[PDB]
């Protein structure tokens, strides 16, 4: 295929409920937003913005949104499994690095800076992997995983030590813009993009409609929020045919990890319906 | 020891947050309750009551409180692990029946009727166990697990088929009154009580102060609610010395399952502090 693939992930029970709660907090704002369509009050424009942000943080990990109860130490042996258990996306990734840590490879992961980067590292300490960060921060393996910010790197204070290609570039959140100059640099080190996408979540909406309407388009923001709200009851659950692949811990993907030139083994990004303002109001009544 | 033992359990991340949310919903009522100490308005008396009930349902399983997103089928192979993952108490019990299913034994479990009973069954379908219910409802193993209501049985429409002792009686919730005539009947079938107690939760409060003050005592209700609210930041986390035992999946308890006459391997119920109305107001400001 194209070198640009999505890897759908699940949602925790907790991740599903937090999203249902985020939507409900913004109930009034959502209706105000679709009602007075053709002015968009900034109280309300930004109420939708923060809603999509919050739903997006949860989609990757609930700790990005709700701090307390978070382990004082992210370094203890129990942490990696605790984090995977509370994010369907971390789980998928944990299964993925379990396959690639079997290889002599440099693998790149791009995600937003800050706490996302520290939880990614916390997680990867449960894999047999070297971890390199390029933000001056942090807490005998054949595979090294490099963590890059999606919001600006700085290769002249932190150069790539590698020497070798990145065999794949993983996108953890929809915060990553793979077209930016810094990521296009990583992709050409001598590279396939796999995007971790929680099914039927804001990630899935941003991705799919990101084609459709592009930019900070009118119909983009609207379709993305209508679908986030409406699809909110089908968060993180896979079509029945994907289920054995994930249950078998993504072993399905080994031939593709062997030959990254081989066609992507999984279905293309599932289409998301175009929803009406009336579609959204129905969903909110229920 | 005495034949009456507690088995501390953990809390899910989701279980901890729901409890922090339940407490917060009742913020005003809690302060009103401790403020006008010496009249207790029933609006407020029952506000504390429902708070303790809700915190107690979550302590056993969040689905007892928040229905939606709950699997349409509790019978599919994935369900048992999904339920254990969302209740620290279900996890402990899953580890426990993994030990005892190795034996030719009749094991009794008492819990409140209704959905608690259906989730207990859902869970136990993931163990190599026979399951008997005595409430006319439901969805080659050496071990059979009998599920009894804590709120009245009816042995003359559903008699014990067993023929053999119950080697242990497990208390899932604080809903079980082991002194009642129906449970004292089960305990003498020719029996050790193990109580599944989520640490630093309402279960732990009811148990500990249930000695202390007994009955629907004045100081009982008050100490139990002050401690629930105050201990709400230390929900479900074990003292460091218990952690390998649970990490090693309760294998620590096998010699005791071999000889139930052997002294209980674990520490006695940890004491809970007596808290002030001023103690509770501090906790609520923070």
Image (spheres, coloured by chain):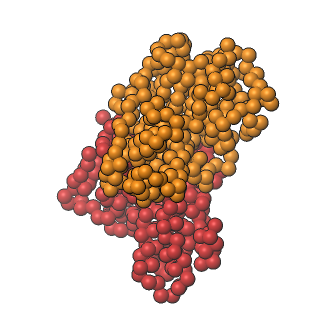
Chain colours: A orange, B red
* Residue located at (62% from left, 44% from top): B244
Q: Is residue A227 visible?
A: yes
Count all numbered tags in the image, as a single digit: 0
Residue farthest to the right, as pictured: A157
- Residue A220's place in the image compared with A27, above or below, is above
Quadrant showing the C terminus of chain B:
bottom right
Q: Position of residue A60 (x, y in %)?
A: 54, 40
- Residue A73's place in the image compared with B285, above or below, is above
Q: Position of residue A69 (x, y in %)?
A: 60, 53
Q: Position of residue B236 (x, y in %)?
A: 55, 55
- Residue B222's place in the image compared with B13, above or below, is below
- Residue A254's place in the image compared with B251, above or below, is above
Residue farthest to the bottom, as pictured: B38
Front in this rendered view, residue B163 or B220 = B220
* Residue located at (64% from left, 23% from top): A184
Quadrant in which residue B153 is drawn = bottom left
Q: Is residue A198 visible?
A: no
Q: Position of residue A95 (x, y in %)?
A: 53, 29
* Residue located at (75% from left, 28% from top): A155
* Residue located at (45% from left, 57% from top): A29
Q: Is residue A236 left or right of residue B209?
A: left
């Amino acid at each position: 295929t194209s070198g640009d693939y999505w890897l759908p992930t699940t949602m925790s029970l907790y991740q599903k409920e937090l999203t249902d709660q985020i939507v409900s907090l913004h109930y009034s704002d959502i209706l105000r937003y679709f009602e007075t369509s053709h002015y968009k009050e900034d109280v309300i424009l930004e109420s939708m913005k923060t809603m999509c942000l919050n739903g997006s943080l949860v989609a990757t990990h609930p700790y990005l949104l709700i701090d307390h109860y978070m382990p004082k130490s992210l370094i203890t042996r129990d942490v990696p499994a605790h984090l995977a258990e509370n994010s369907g996306k971390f789980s998928v990734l944990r299964d993925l690095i379990n396959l690639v840590q079997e290889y002599e490879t440099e693998t790149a992961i791009v995600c937003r800076p800050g706490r996302t980067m520290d939880l990614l590292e916390a997680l990867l300490l449960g894999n047999k992997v070297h971890i390199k960060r390029y933000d001056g921060h942090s807490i005998d393996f054949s595979c090294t995983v490099h963590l890059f910010s999606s919001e600006g790197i700085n290769f002249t204070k932190y150069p790539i030590k590698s020497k070798a290609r990145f065999d794949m570039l993983i996108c953890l959140d929809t915060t990553v813009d793979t077209s930016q100059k810094d990521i296009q640099y990583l992709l050409q080190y001598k590279a396939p993009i796999v995007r971790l996408v929680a099914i039927n979540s804001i990630d899935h909406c941003r991705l799919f409609f990101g084609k459709k309407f592009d930019k900070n388009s009118r119909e983009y923001l609207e379709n993305v929020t209508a679908a986030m709200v409406i699809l909110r009851d089908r968060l993180g659950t896979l079509p029945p045919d994907l289920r054995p692949i994930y249950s078998q811990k993504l072993h399905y993907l080994v031939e593709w990890l062997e030959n990254p030139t081989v066609p992507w083994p999984l279905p293309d990004i599932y289409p998301l319906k175009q929803y009406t303002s009336m579609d959204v109001e129905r969903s909110l009544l229920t």
